Length: 327
Ligand SMILES: CN1[C@H]2C[C@H](OC(=O)[C@H](CO)c3ccccc3)C[C@@H]1[C@@H](O)C2
Ligand SMILES: O=C(O)CCC(=O)C(=O)O
Ligand SMILES: [Fe+2]
Ligand SMILES: [Sr+2]
Ligand SMILES: [Sr+2]
Image (cartoon, rainbow, N blue to C red; front, side):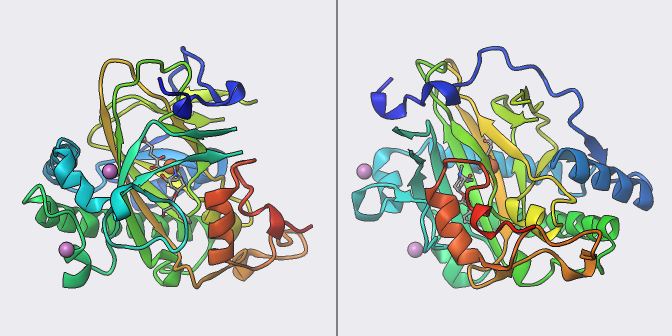
């Protein structure tokens, strides 16, 4: 592979990462209190769980994966239309809601992730936003509009389960804290040397909560510097708690630290729905949960200020929130 994609020695993935047998798989059609309790335990102990029987149509999940795969099969002349000034955009502020193709890496030793990402905003859905989405394939806009609404519906159900678990009023996150919905469609082409590369460097999702749809292996979670493989369940969503939710819960909940490894033989598409605050938001531990026994571990901070650090500084997983740590 090009030296551009060679990860630093310490960040390279070992070849035999074990299946995470203890990754919670939570059936959302269990009794209400059982669902709240199982989600609460997963949030406290892991920060990553899968949801099944989640009420989002399986047919729509399949149709969305199909149209996302069809997009990444488009020829160069079509993909160029989403490359500003002839090259992929960077994950940096301002992060615009119009559709673009993105490149990503780390400036520490600088290297690139073995990944192409299509990203666009999804909320609120209006003609201007959808008109800024891919023109091809022809059905992308119709399918992904329906998917966007359904994934948001499921995310808001999960956030209300989280509210009940924490003792926050229902709808606590149904406001500026969930206003941005970025859909990141990740394409991992086959890689000649998986031992040297990463599809996605180890990270927290910096936002509130992410729902991830996958049908192939490659996703790994950090649990004593131990990585585990997250079983692909094509009809499930992987729920990743973001660094923003870790802060708001005053670390009562864990954030998901995860990475993606490359494959030498097959390509892989994943669909990540990033829900989180507007860039104008102030983030702090929920005052409702604080006491002398539970003092705040973070001072209030600008989500925009956090965002700039989160997207630039990859010296540590929580580099984005280190400046705001107290007590
Ligand atoms: C591997 N990279 C991580 C960092 C960055 O994430 C973002 O760009 C999100 C997109 O919502 C973001 C979160 C919080 C603040 C700003 C941006 C781009 C991608 C994502 O898949 C996660
Ligand atoms: O491709 C995956 O399974 C992970 C995607 C992801 O972590 C992300 O987009 O943030
Ligand atoms: Fe992620
Ligand atoms: Sr180009
Ligand atoms: Sr347009």
